Length: 49
DNA sequence: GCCGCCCTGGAGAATCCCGGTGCCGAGGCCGCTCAATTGGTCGTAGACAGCTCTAGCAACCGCTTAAACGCACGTACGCGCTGTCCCCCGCGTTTTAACCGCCAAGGGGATTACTTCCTAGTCTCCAGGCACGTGTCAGATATATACATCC
Image (cartoon, rainbow, N blue to C red):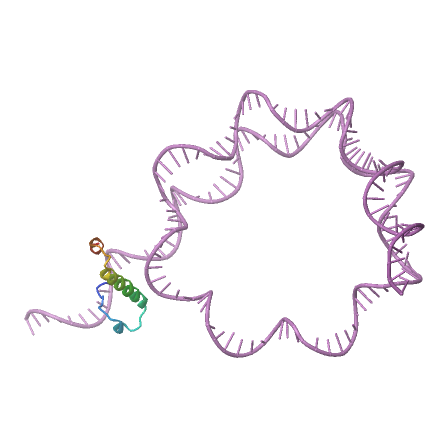
């Protein structure tokens, strides 16, 4: 019900359904966020949008 | 004497069934309407008969000879088993475009009716192209006869 949202960890999850969604979120968000943070070819407009 | 708790009865509301009435799919009925029917006439397609000549057919012959058949051997290939690895399938997740519903105007094309004229059918006459047969002629082929030569 979006009120029982839990702050979890990979070892705290174990093996449940939807772990591929967690892997996809981790890969996309973390990899692309640190890519746009660490790239020197990033303007101020891109980082603020 | 006063106050709180457990047991049981009749009235108010929800649901199933039936009857009256309105709406969707299909069939009977009516009206147009054009194509099938009927009746008559005539030309000709085809049936029938007749004669001639050639191919086929049943059953036999005889001869030749090459193909078919039988047999032995051998070995190459079909097939079965095993390994392996790789690639396709199943599944979960994310994207994306098919699908449906919308403009906005305009052209293409299917009908209905009408006009016109060019071109193809039809008829008559004629002539030349096609089919068949034959005389003749030049190229190809085989041998007759004369000259140089080896033993």
